[PDB]
Image: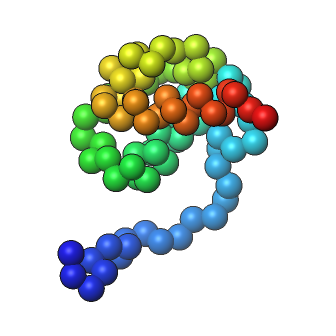
């Protein structure tokens, strides 16, 4: 907007990620929703469409879920989330 106008609210947090270090297949009901916020805050998504109530996937269900599915549970944001999950499982 003008002279910053961003980054003036909650700028502290350094305790690793609850979903960092473990594959997407061994994720918990919390880790999942926890990973979403990360992609929702990075993609600048309003996050006023996704249905967290529908995201009951613990972990194995997320990696097993389908593309169109993630798009119906996380709105149009799924298209972006899937791309990420596709790399997590892919591994090196």
Q: Residue at x 58, y 14 (%)?
A: 64
Q: Is residue 54 left or right of residue 66?
A: left
Q: Is residue 5 left or right of residue 69?
A: left
Along the line of sight, the residue nearer the viewer: 50 or 42 = 42
Q: Is residue 27 left or right of residue 83?
A: right
Question: Can you say whether 90 is above or below 14 in the image?
Answer: above
In the orientation shown, which residue stands out farthest toward the right?
Answer: 92
Quarter the N terminus occupies: bottom left
Quarter the C terminus occupies: top right
Q: Residue at x 27, y 47 (%)?
A: 46
Q: Residue at x 53, y 40 (%)?
A: 35
In the image, residue 52 lies at what x, y percent?
A: 37, 30
Question: Can you say whether 58 is above or below 16 in the image?
Answer: above
Along the line of sight, the residue nearer the viewer: 85 or 56 = 85
Question: Can you say whether 7 is above or below 62 in the image?
Answer: below
Res 53 → quadrant: top left
Q: Is residue 14 left or right of residue 53?
A: right
Task: Give the colouring mode of the picture.
Answer: rainbow
In the image, residue 77 lies at what x, y percent?
A: 36, 35
In the orientation shown, which residue stands out farthest toward the left?
Answer: 1
Q: Is residue 52 visible?
A: no
In the image, residue 70 lies at what x, y percent?
A: 42, 22
Q: Is residue 34 visible?
A: yes
How many numbered discs? 0
In the image, residue 71 lies at what x, y percent?
A: 36, 24
């Amino acid at each position: 907007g003008s002279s910053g106008s961003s980054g003036q609210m909650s700028l502290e947090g350094t305790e690793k990620a609850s979903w960092l270090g473990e594959q997407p297949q061994f994720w918990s009901k919390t880790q999942v929703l926890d990973w979403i916020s990360y992609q929702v805050e990075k993609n600048k998504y309003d996050a006023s469409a996704i249905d967290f109530s529908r995201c009951d996937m613990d972990g194995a269900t997320l990696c097993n879920c389908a593309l169109e599915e993630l798009r119906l549970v996380f709105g149009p944001l799924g298209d972006q989330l899937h791309a990420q999950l596709r790399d997590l499982t892919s591994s090196s």
